Image 1 (tube, each protein chain N blue to C red):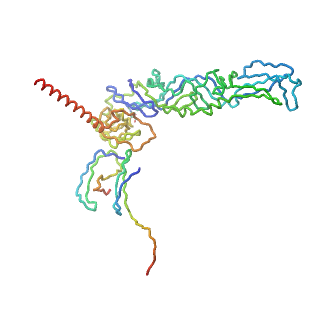
Image 2 (cartoon, rainbow over the protein chains, first blue to last red):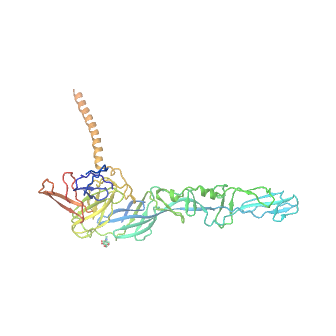
Image 3 (spheres, rainbow over the protein chains, first blue to last red):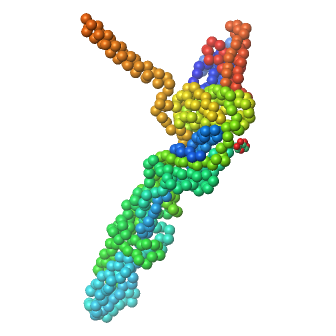
Amino acid sequence: FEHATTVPNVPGIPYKALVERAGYAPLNLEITVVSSELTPSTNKEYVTC
Amino acid sequence: FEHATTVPNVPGIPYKALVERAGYAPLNLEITVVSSELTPSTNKEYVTCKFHTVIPSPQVKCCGSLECKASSKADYTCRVFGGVYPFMWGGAQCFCDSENTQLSEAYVEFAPDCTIDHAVALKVHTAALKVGLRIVYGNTTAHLDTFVNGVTPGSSRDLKVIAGPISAAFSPFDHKVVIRKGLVYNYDFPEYGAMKPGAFGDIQASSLDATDIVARTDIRLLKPSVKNIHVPYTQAVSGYEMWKNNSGRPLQETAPFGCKIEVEPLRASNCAYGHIPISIDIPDAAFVRSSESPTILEVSCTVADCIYSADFGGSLTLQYKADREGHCPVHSHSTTAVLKEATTHVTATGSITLHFSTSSPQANFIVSLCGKKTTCNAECKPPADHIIGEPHKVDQEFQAAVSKTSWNWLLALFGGASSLIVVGLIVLVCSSMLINTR
Amino acid sequence: SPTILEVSCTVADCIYSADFGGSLTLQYKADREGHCPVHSHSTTAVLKE
Ligand SMILES: *[C@@H]1O[C@H](CO)[C@@H](O)[C@H](O)[C@H]1NC(C)=O
């Protein structure tokens, strides 16, 4: 079942929802962002000291 | 007690009814069509296969005449040639220089492999339906094999079941049928003797071992123009092979109503079409008096998560406070929703769950529990899955198939139009009375 | 899935904060014993369980 929702980007804070397919029982679904990783592409120019 | 009802002809899909007999308690009764056989009466017209077209050894008579008589062989073609001079391995075969005579003969016969690779032509008359019925009443099962003509009783002797005529006679077979190796085709074959070369039915016989074989394969015996002894013959192709190359698809793949065709008596099996009126003379011993059935003092139906679907998508709970522990028949009194369970157990108090399948968007049917009737009310959601592997247990109505919200909207708009009409006519009535008074 | 014949929520000592502050009790009657998804259908209040 394709279910689309929106979660916050806060680490922790479980986001809870029900997926409710018609013929079947409501099903719990929570998504938690355990960690996040902004990794930019870095190009090395030089080293100084 | 006699009970007359109408069941669908679909295989499976139990039809459930509640026989109510005065003071003899409600009796559950479900009928399942476990099998169906549409068996027409078939008359064998002929058999056919490839022909062998055997050419006998030529006869030569030199300085003489060699006219030939008629023969009873299948498509016997004989022709006399008067200018021959045959040559075997060893030179000339007779003395006479130019007045020789060769007899060319050519007749067809059944191929050696026609014991399997052959086709049978049948004329098919009207077909009679025979259904296997699993009928359970009370706590007793019964398996019957009933003709659906309308007068023949069932196979079982303890209960009498009479299945009335089908609403619409189907008969998937046309008047002419060809069976080839278990495959059934609706082909318009020629009659016995009204045959044409090249088409299906070049060679015909009553049986494969029959000596009365008739054929009209177009054999032309040409004149021998070579040194060696030869019978130059030309012929049309086998109509069996031509028909086999373009036979199309058999009726095992093109039959309507999901029929499933066999060949040994040539019956169509499990054809879901029409309705069977059925009357059952239930024995009096099956019924029990209403004193021995538990009485439901009060019942309440609460139904949640209803889905109108082919499967049993709805579930309703009956809360009850009866007076004695015992078994009740549970029934749904609508033609749109059907209960899965037909008999439940009843404690002094409690609740029982029941699965039902419906086609209406609204679950506004009446459920009976030892004859005590309650009304359920909910809104049944459309199913999410689109395709299911089992057929629908119920048919689709018009009043049921329109939801209560949509019924409210259409009735509100129609009543608004009618109300403006009524107000207009009332204002004309009042104005006309005022102006004729004045 | 079990079906709920009757449900009613009474909530005591609610307090709007980051912590799960507030206790709502569902009094329920259901025919079959089992396990059940529970959910809050508001984007403002989220359940712990
Ligand atoms: C059929 O037999 C069962 C056996 O469990 C019994 O409970 C039930 O009452 C019987 N039905 C009738 C109609 O007597």
